[PDB]
Image (cartoon, rainbow over all chains, first blue to last red; front, side, top):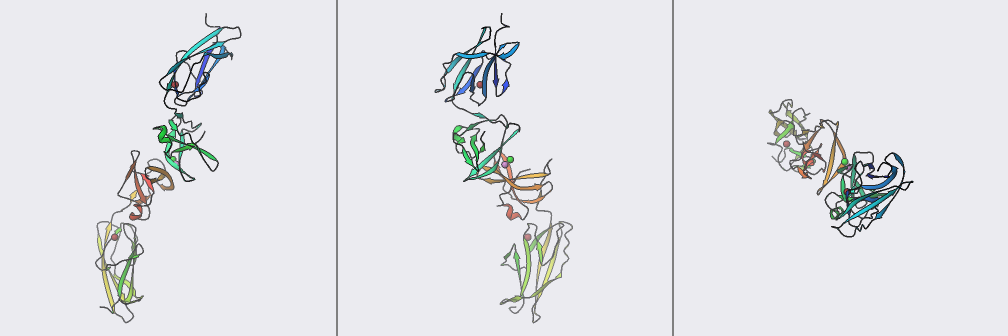
Length: 175
Length: 174
Ligand SMILES: [Br-]
Ligand SMILES: [Br-]
Ligand SMILES: [Cl-]
Ligand SMILES: [Hg+2]
């Protein structure tokens, strides 16, 4: 009998998901900082796991990873993660998802309001409006080195590859 | 001949080393035409002057003794005769031909927007320019387009045809 058991919820990029966490398969990039209740996928979408007392009670329930062997150092490896949620009467629900380690971290660009995202080119210390624009939800490679000019931070990006992002001269304001 | 007035001209500010006599110019339908100072179809200012003689650069009086030019209809030509007079009363005349042409400018259509964005191109980078045009504006367009990221751009200038070749003001073609 399941109805009194904890319910495991998840959000992807802020949006509650209707599919069960159990049996999900995620991509995570080599070198990413992975926590089984809060991690970032290969495309840069934040995934957050949480739980409630039951299907009919949204009150917070405790949830923890009872098995998290995940290691992000090497691509082409997968790991299963098992979560267990426990309610106040001590009833349990577990969910198991699979994490695939992939090569590259992309980031998802959020206009946070606007449909359109402005880009810039930097020449010496002059920042010029570029004609290229991105749409909210576009996925790009981002160079690891930001640049600050007139007290504003900029990140160098490319839809092609990480290496291209290091010299693309297409910049967005850092979030 | 040497004691007679000499007729000079400039095009876009540069003194010309060809006689004004026998020149053929293009002038755009609808333009204001003055035979001593006018703007050709490509936007270059042409200015006529005269001097007392081959060796005396002192100003000499020059006027159109025959100017039937009418710019209202393209495909018509007119001859213009200029006569210069020196202070001893010696005369020189020059005759040039004016062709009335249709506009050598193109019209920019915003296809919706009142404003038309322009760009600057450096290598393969396209940057937003601050210059804007209004729908219906007329500009000179360079004959060489440039394509970047599969988008075609045309290089333009409101001033002259020649300026459009190096303005670094571009619009999206068509
Ligand atoms: Br994923
Ligand atoms: Br001409
Ligand atoms: Cl833009
Ligand atoms: Hg721009």
